[PDB]
Image 1 (tube, each protein chain N blue to C red):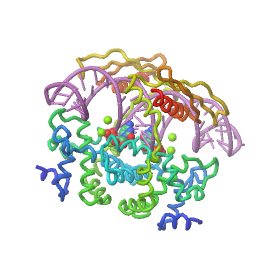
Image 2 (tube, chains in turn yellow, purple, blue, green):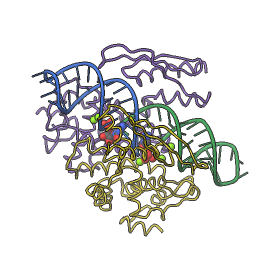
Image 3 (cartoon, chains in turn purple, brown, cyan, blue):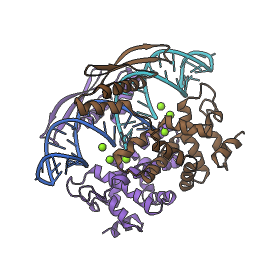
Image 4 (cartoon, rainbow over the protein chains, first blue to last red):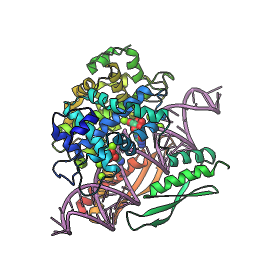
Length: 218
Length: 220
RNA sequence: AAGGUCAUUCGCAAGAGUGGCCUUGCG
RNA sequence: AAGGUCAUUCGCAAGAGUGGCCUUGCG
Ligand SMILES: Nc1ccn([C@@H]2O[C@H](COP(=O)(O)O)[C@@H](O)[C@H]2O)c(=O)n1
Ligand SMILES: Nc1ccn([C@@H]2O[C@H](COP(=O)(O)O)[C@@H](O)[C@H]2O)c(=O)n1
Ligand SMILES: [Mg+2]
Ligand SMILES: [Mg+2]
Ligand SMILES: [Mg+2]
Ligand SMILES: [Mg+2]
Ligand SMILES: [Mg+2]
Ligand SMILES: [Mg+2]
């Protein structure tokens, strides 16, 4: 089964016990699972992104690069790099069916496995990772698709003008449990907006977006 | 320059000295060439070095165990400790302001990105050189339990296990100039209450929480 | 990391550094 | 990442994962 992934990955695993381990959720096999490779994989991949970022950025200033890094190492962006490999079909998982958290953890653990299996060659694993995603990463930046952080953008403009911060207050929580939706107000001076999501923090994000809209004509 | 010293201490000689100079230079000294960029890459690079060492050598590879260790090992305090070996502060070029733990912590992670770039971006060699100096020294600190304790975190899990409550920190005073201050903070759980001091709220809270921890486990 | 803020150094402003404070996001 | 808690899943417990909330630490 792994052979199809190894074609996409373009790498033949010498020890297949690792590749299986990184693909296995603890609900499948308790004693063998991706947990420890996800820990190694993060620091490994987060290093790749930053290393790539410092090389190809016209502006190398830390203030410019760090928020750009914040999105590229995010779990959501890892889910997009996973779509290229179609990871959701390769995972061994039983209960707690696949979601963006599980995928991002496998993707992190996946590269740690390659690092280990190659005999801890960081230089090669880097270029193998680059081979796949280098253009894809440079794509999003050059073509300007980067998840915009609205709660941050908002409060920076409000403090720019009135030297104050927007206030996010809850309205209601609606749904049975995990289907529950949050409704949150966002207020700056005389302006109020709304937003919603599966969490408070998410509901505060959409409300923050609608609020930047609300000051245009202002 | 005088860079011959640090190179021998580092067991590595730079092909580009301008790159080595840039790692030791604060923005104040040179508004043109300084360490800001290498600090960025250096964090991600050196953070990876530590994490790879933990997963490898320690018998307990369980994540919940390893992550707290990482927190101390990648910290600013621990980088200042590792930097004392290299005697970095005497090589640091700075215009205005004292050289503090922040600057040294910045220079340290930045200094390693310099070695990284100068090696032709060889991670295997650089990681080896990092272990060359610090591997046993780091591993000995864990073995001997020289890891710094987190008192705000320990205390909270202590109370939530017993009283199902959280400690509450109150600020009882402030004294001194605005740039150099003094913080006295009280920590409270049930009727048990202690004080603590620090140059920041959190630093004083860690001291207050520590006293509470000692007071508690005694009484409990 | 980023923004506002007080203090301070750059003779003041501009901006920048460092320490304190509040807040936001990423891992 | 860690702890408490609500829900949910492995027939309960134990232990663990997932979604929610409060909190704490590190980069
Ligand atoms: N609160 C923080 C602390 C660090 N960071 C990230 O970690 C990097 C390294 O920060 P340090 O200067 O603390 O080592 C930053 O450049 C930034 O990308 C962050 O994004 N948010
Ligand atoms: N709040 C957080 C989140 C993540 N982390 C670090 O990031 C690692 C991976 O976390 P993720 O699951 O978010 O990718 C953790 O094992 C821990 O070392 C942290 O130290 N503090
Ligand atoms: Mg995890
Ligand atoms: Mg991660
Ligand atoms: Mg900085
Ligand atoms: Mg750092
Ligand atoms: Mg900053
Ligand atoms: Mg966790």
